Image (spheres, coloured by chain):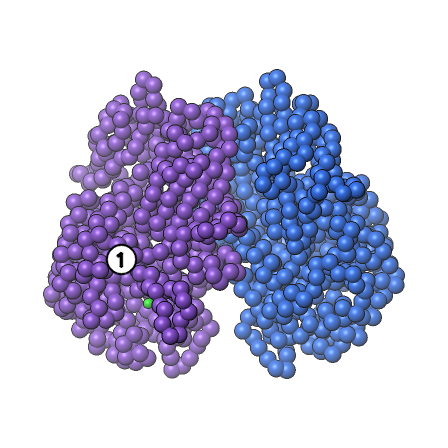
Chain colours: A blue, B purple
Amino acid sequence: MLYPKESETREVKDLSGVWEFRTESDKNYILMPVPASFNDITQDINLRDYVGRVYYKKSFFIPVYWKERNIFLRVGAAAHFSEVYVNGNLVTKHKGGFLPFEAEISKFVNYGQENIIEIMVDNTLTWDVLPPGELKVIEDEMHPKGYKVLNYYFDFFNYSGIHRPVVIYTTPKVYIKDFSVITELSNNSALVKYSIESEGNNFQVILRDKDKNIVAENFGKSGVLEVKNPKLWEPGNPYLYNLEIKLLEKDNFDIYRMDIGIRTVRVEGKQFLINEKPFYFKGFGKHEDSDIRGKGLDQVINIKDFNLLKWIGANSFRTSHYPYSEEILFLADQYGIAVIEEAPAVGLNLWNRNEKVFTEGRVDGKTLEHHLEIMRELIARDKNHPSVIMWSVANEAATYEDGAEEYFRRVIEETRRLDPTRPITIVENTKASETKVSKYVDVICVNRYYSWYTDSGDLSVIEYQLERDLREWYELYRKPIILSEFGADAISGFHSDPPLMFTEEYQQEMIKRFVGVLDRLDFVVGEHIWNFADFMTKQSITRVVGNKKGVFTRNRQPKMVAHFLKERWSKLPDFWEK
Amino acid sequence: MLYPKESETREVKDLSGVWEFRTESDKNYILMPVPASFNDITQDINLRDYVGRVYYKKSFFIPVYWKERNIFLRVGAAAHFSEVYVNGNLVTKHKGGFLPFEAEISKFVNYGQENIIEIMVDNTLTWDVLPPGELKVIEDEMHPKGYKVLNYYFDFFNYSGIHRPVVIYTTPKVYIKDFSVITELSNNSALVKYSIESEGNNFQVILRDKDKNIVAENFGKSGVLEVKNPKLWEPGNPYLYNLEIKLLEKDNFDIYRMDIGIRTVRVEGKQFLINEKPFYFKGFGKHEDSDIRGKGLDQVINIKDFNLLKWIGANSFRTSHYPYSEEILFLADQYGIAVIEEAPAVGLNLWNRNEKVFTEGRVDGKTLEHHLEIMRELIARDKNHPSVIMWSVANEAATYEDGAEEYFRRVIEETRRLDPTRPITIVENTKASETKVSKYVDVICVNRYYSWYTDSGDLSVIEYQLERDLREWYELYRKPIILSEFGADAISGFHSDPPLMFTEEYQQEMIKRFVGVLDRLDFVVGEHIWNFADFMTKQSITRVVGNKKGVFTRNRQPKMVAHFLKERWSKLPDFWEK
Ligand SMILES: [Cl-]
Ligand SMILES: [Cl-]
């Protein structure tokens, strides 16, 4: 499914705005913005911590002239289970809170009249949705009848609601359903190879440069476009060409356009190559999180975040720990930021080797089935973005378990089959010698928190422990390694010398000592600090109103270590043969 | 001009989203969200502090089926001077940064094809725009050639950009252009009297209650709708009826709907009556201000703000110091919050009696002309909102000057002529015996900061000074009095005992002592604390990154005094015969 875009042949109507909202088995509505998480909008603590079904409702008018058009209703994201009703008719259901879903609804609309859309969203986690969790009953001596808790083991808050825009769009009855683009370098040219999915068959395809000059054209539902003297897309030079696809049939006419970038990505030895040059990742793990709206899409915050990425000198980030909005990937295309996009397989770990995760009752064949469908949906959505340069299949799963090996072999095999054009990783906090899964990926991503979660407060252990660990990863697997997470919680304004945990000084010193180690290791091709910004988590005595490891505050202002990273990364080239 | 609303006969296309953006005489664009202020979006300090013209650009497609429709392009707000181009054609110009403007553009569009909209916005202040300011050249021994400053004397930052949504909407060629509604109480019924502006003449008008029951109907371009057993709108009971207007002609058909509220407002003696009951204002001066987006409209923030208003027990606010977005007034209608809406005549004061403001060179006949046009635009926009219950013509002008008397007599006279159905005020910080203007309004609004700006730190003077002052206002003018501003800057987390300026304790103690005085004065009908939330100002040694007098932080979380006000206001009735 293609991102909804207006053209000569397609209308788009955005239903974002103020909706009516209620919780299960309640008749009274309140007002609720869309897109947004509902948790922080009100002062009702029982809604903040609500677990169950909520219902959104809105009126909309369909123009009579949309008859004899396809009418699609698209929901960008709703966490985690959703059902969509048009005038009381169920038009689609969806499982998974971080990818879009849509249905054709012309059969159910009142033309030239009022219509009602209702969207049910259920935030109840189970062990066969990603990320997983479990609702548990607690009726003991200290809890009243009916006390229940939603348990989950990922470290970000279970925000719920409609997190990305709801839109209605039209197409002709015979229309461009999808297309695939692959770019190759050939002699002094680039090739853009394409295939179009449609019931139609007569297509003209045109490629235009930045100045609207036509640089290539082809008649054909599949084909190759040759670009002589191409300008390649890469961090530091985000050149985009505009691909125009025109269906020209007897009764149907359809146009779809997308900006694409010409680049190659390849792993060879201990090098991560973009356009055949050795890349060095400088960046962050991020989160879709901001004040008040929770996980809701906000283009103000998105553009602010990319300007901060360019300001600090980052060239990349990982979409920890789930696919982000398409909007963020289009921006990464424009700004020239390399993206590792990650499936929502986070929380597959009970920090305890006595509780097994990959076992009947928890992560099983049903979870695997969902994970495989997720990879198919994710690659289908994002396969044409130049900014996505790697897929991450999971974050900190219990990869030391025997059952994790067969599980992830299947996930990894399916991902590569779906997209052979990008490398694959998995983000590990398991010990190097214990993971049964990292031997199957292209690039190793390791999260390490020496002197924070272990030997807390003792910065002196970092060089000893980190160098020994990373050398063992390389000795066992002989793959490029990204230090995919490291950092320390810092309360803005907490200062100390000597540095103490939770101060800005400790965060900067820890990060500084980690990267001094990486500079001595020629097989380390990247550093991603956790996290870009402070974000909300569930409440616990270990979380000082959320996770405070941001390099920026939640309102997008820098802590001390942001300036250290700006100075370091201004000296580090994007392409660096270590 | 009516708020753009979809119906059976009208389409609305929202152009908000990501636009291209550049500054004057520069050819390279960056990305910029709309709606938003541009100042805090980037890390370019020279754009943050930019003074001059900026240019927004976006492509849009017009459906061929919009031929033979009116096509209107509406800009919700752009601060402060703006020009709108459709495919290079100037379709309208506008002066004033806080009210909407529109043009019919069907003559300039390419049907079924790409179109380009460009919007120029100029943030350069002058003495004949509201709020006023002046660009000054400073080429002396300590400033290089070309150093210039924009001087202005209002205490909020001169954020600029497109602050409210840009939309395109259709109507039939003969259409409902405007309508006026007035509500009266008669015996046991309410009357909704209406007049419609249109080139058409055959109208059916229907009024529906909350459950869609038809409670009144009338055929006629003007008329009266009788509601037996009306449910009145008021704070604490925001009942809205839906007014449906249907134009039924030979070749044209048009429907427009609006929720309205049935209430009366009247000043009599020292009482402010809503629905013939004595009201007591409990609330705030607000600002259109939030993190990152500046003055840009954000419905997440708006709904959050109204939930906080209901949580703390407020029943009212003033739109300090300019008209707010229509969106906020529709929400105030839904939530039952009484609004004093204020014209942007703030900054008409050089805190210095040697520099006259109402004089040739500063506030003169050109400024007055703009002010009068502003009142006409403001009442035309908001005349049908039940939540607006009073107009404020200015905030803290230099009303002690001889020239201020003739200026404001004309403003006040024109406001009353335009809308005889709502009382009029002006918000004063002049001394009671010195203002030449308050004798002409219906309700006195006085801002007082004893122990903050005067006798700084000495809370012991409050009762002595405030009671004497307010008794003199009543003795001179014999009108109801609202304490329209009072408060203290408080940094969140700054605490002290004994209380010190800038601590949360000092803010709470000051506010507590002020309202203890008000409770002893039967002619005081309201308390508005300055401010609802921390907001940005220009930089100065008196502003600790903006104005810190918020009862809530800028991210909408409560300070200590928020809990004091919640407890007080939970005990104070909305209707209180003092
Ligand atoms: Cl962490
Ligand atoms: Cl102030």
At horizontal 73% and vertical 43% (from top left) the residue drawn is: A375
Residue at the spot of label 1: B127
Residue A435 percent coordinates (x, y): 83, 58
Report if the beta carbon of the residue with label 1 is closer than 8 angstroms to ligand 2.
no
Q: Position of residue B278 (x, y in %)?
A: 21, 54
Q: Quadrant of ligand 2?
A: bottom left
Q: Is residue B273 left or right of residue B382?
A: left
Residue A20 x %, y %: 46, 42
Q: Is residue A16 left or right of residue A210?
A: left
Q: Residue furthest right?
A: A476
Q: Residue at x 81, y 52 (%)?
A: A267
Residue in the picture at 81% in, 64% down:
A522
Density class for disc 1 (Cα within 10 Å; few <14, some 14-19, many ≥20) is: some
Q: Is residue A25 above or below residue A495?
A: above
Front residue of this view, candidates A70 and A44: A70
State left or right for residue A544 relative to residue A317.
left
